Amino acid sequence: PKYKIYTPGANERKFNNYMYMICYGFVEDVKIRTIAAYPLGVGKSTSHPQDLLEELCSLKVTVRRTAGATEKIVFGSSGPLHHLLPWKKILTGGSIFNAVKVCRNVDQIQLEKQQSLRIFFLSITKLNDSGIYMIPRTMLEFRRNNAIAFNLLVYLKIKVASFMLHLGNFVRRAGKYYSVEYCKRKIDRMKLQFSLGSIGGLSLHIKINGVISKRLFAQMGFQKNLCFSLMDINPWLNRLTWNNSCEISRVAAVLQPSVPREFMIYDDVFIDNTGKILKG
Amino acid sequence: PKYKIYTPGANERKFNNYMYMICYGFVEDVKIRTIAAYPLGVGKSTSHPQDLLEELCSLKVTVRRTAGATEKIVFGSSGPLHHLLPWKKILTGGSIFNAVKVCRNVDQIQLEKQQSLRIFFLSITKLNDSGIYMIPRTMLEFRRNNAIAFNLLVYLKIKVASFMLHLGNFVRRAGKYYSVEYCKRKIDRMKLQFSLGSIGGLSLHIKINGVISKRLFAQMGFQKNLCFSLMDINPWLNRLTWNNSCEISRVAAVLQPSVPREFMIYDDVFIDNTGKILKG
């Protein structure tokens, strides 16, 4: 059993009073049915990660399968706390997660048997704040006619894989025909910086170090720091980053139409090697 | 390239003017990047399935990867229609699906290359109506304190797998202690009948042939016919039923607490071999 710490805001040199944690374990008969993830959230703590890991391994964590609109996994924790007291609410009062996010093989978890979680890894993300900022889901799911979606394609080395995320929408000017090198230089003024976290398993963290338009900035809640979790973007790929080393190998900007019909008209514009990856 | 027809309401002997369709294809470079599903929806048609299959194979179907809050796949179709004219809106004006529902390996689909869908199977569900009835997602995601969730666990032979679905909530009477044989006989009066469809890939269809309480019936929109798609319940398991033969082997009722905290108190009640599986 081991841990790994991630510090997405390392270049900001801030003191990190907060720790986001997520752990992974075998779902076992009280043999191994599947692997699952147990997101503990953010606690205000400065404890040593070995103390946190060891107190977590002392807990009895139950795994109960259920359903709503979709299959769900309920975690119940049991045992006295000391170091884990900042995560006291989550660890002591049960928590529920969509099986798709936290378990690939929910279909293999038993109902006639009791199931426990045997933790083998603890993932930490150091934060100087109790909240991380993610663009609201309603706004990211928004589509407009005659619009260009500003998306990023992050390549990850772990074979090699990619995932795509969306920042917002530019206006597709009527009849105006927008050049690649044009856009690229509009994106370059944003001076986007990318670093990895482990929020949800794997998170991509974005700092806006340059200039960005008011109409686009508003789409991102006027926040110079944005966080996107791979658990939201691609739960299947996210599973492969659990207990596995990752780095960003390459980031492209992919400019696309927003609404589906306009995909028949406009092809993707692929701007390679955008922003800058922080040595981390 | 082949097709398969499903008739979930076969024991009702109704004339089926409507066909729900969903097809599967390799996502190819214009080599094979992944498998994807293309849900076409419901059309008012009586065409032969070989005519539908052959006209579908005549189309140029493009596969474009994009993102919103989560990774998405946009389908574009191209070619003149005759038999597929009931699906004219979907086939000719683009459509967008969460990658998690329609593609396991979205991360492998290219952006610097064009991608097409090479269809190898067409799945049909005969319906006597243009709409299928699914309990609203808001209502299925609802949780109450001191409540018993009425859920079903469907076993499928294809190795063997299961999936869980939720009908609604009973009230957990204060201090009253509800017996297994009690509940079982309350469920048996409902005379639930289960049959398979292919809505979303695999659908479980439920007909209420007996008696059911007003407070519970209201939770299911007062509908004697309910449909649950495996694409909503477990997108990962759903993938294994694409182009693969399935039958229901066994159905249990699993009575559970609703809210997560109460999972620490109340264990699951497992009522085996509930309802009846229609020979289909």
Image (tube, coloured by chain):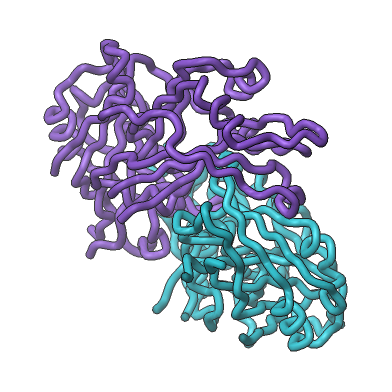
Chain colours: A purple, B cyan
Percent coordinates x, y for residue B159 in the rendering:
39, 79
Q: Residue B270 is drawn in which quadrant? A: bottom left
* Residue A59 appears anywhere in the view: yes
Q: Against B221, is A254 above or below?
A: above
The residue drawn where x is 45% and y is 33% is: A274
Percent coordinates x, y for residue B195 in the rendering:
64, 77
Q: Against A47, is B168 above or below?
A: below
Q: Against A214, is B33 above or below?
A: below
- The image shows a total of numbered marks equal to 0
Seen in the image, is B197 located left or right of residue A58? right
Percent coordinates x, y for residue B125 in the rendering:
72, 76
Seen in the image, is B36 located left or right of residue A192? right
The residue drawn where x is 76% and y is 67% is: B78
* Residue B211 appears anywhere in the view: no
Residue sitting nearer the eye, B24 or B223:
B24
Q: Which corner quadrant holds the N terminus of chain A?
A: top left
The residue drawn where x is 53% and y is 49% is: B148
Residue sitting nearer the eye, A204 or A279:
A279
Q: Residue B20 is drawn in which quadrant? A: bottom right
Residue sitting nearer the eye, B272 or A232:
A232
Q: Which corner quadrant holds the C terminus of chain A?
A: top left
The residue drawn where x is 74% and y is 88% is: B50
Percent coordinates x, y for residue A228 in the rendering:
46, 33
Q: Against B129, is A55 above or below?
A: above
